[PDB]
Length: 372
Ligand SMILES: [N+]
Image (tube, rainbow, N blue to C red; front, side, top):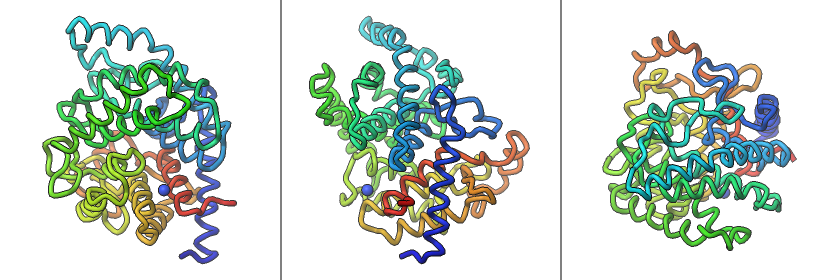
């Protein structure tokens, strides 16, 4: 496995991962995506924050993870009226526009950071349900602390799970993305199987809608035995392993899990560095730390420890002088011609990306390698 040279380097990157996340956590509890990247700074995403929170919870910083869940909960409780209004609009048969939906970017004080017409996404609400239930289970916490916020997210996802929206990468609003459906599934199954939430009025509805999501993925989201990027597509996306671990469309030992890991490795993994999708031109379509961590996590869960370690080593090799993990690296580019214009518009690649550090902590924990 690992010699004391490798173990010391991986332990130190875990410690630094914890420090980077907790140093940049907003005073109100939000995890920012990237404190220094021009286009992300000043905003929080539930997607980034939920995976970040899960790495922190595994690391054992109950206080930091708790303040994130407090922040999300309070932000969601403040949208109780908005969600109620959207649902009433549905009940009058007046399907609300993407422009009226709950936002993707949040300011640290819980306001819309962006206009959902341009970035409408439902995945982050599902990831938060997954994250908060997993945290409470891990540390024996009372979910009543966050329940009113959970109620808002559940009511919203039960109404809007089957709507087309932008993917994790803010593309293709007209499509229904299998890793978005997967994130919602993971959230709904988490709350629907949670004994502390057995008396919630939506308890049964969450498992019935999760079953609906799996029906839709079985009908339109599987080709040649593997998951696909969006319903009705043939291609894969680096996000798809999240549909196995942790969101649970299929278990790790399922043939569709195996074939999805194989298809992602073949189409998108170059030397351990995983690309988002074949057409990606963002910074030339580089190799994403969080996707190499996600594939590694899935390989560990399937009993492929070696394949998991190889992806972990690849990630650790992308750490800069200070131990910071970038969003992505250009060792292989899908569209090298596109990179300069991105560096010109937005500057050098987001570093650190807190989500890179969160995913590092999860994969290190899955391999039993966090400092003792
Ligand atoms: N696991």
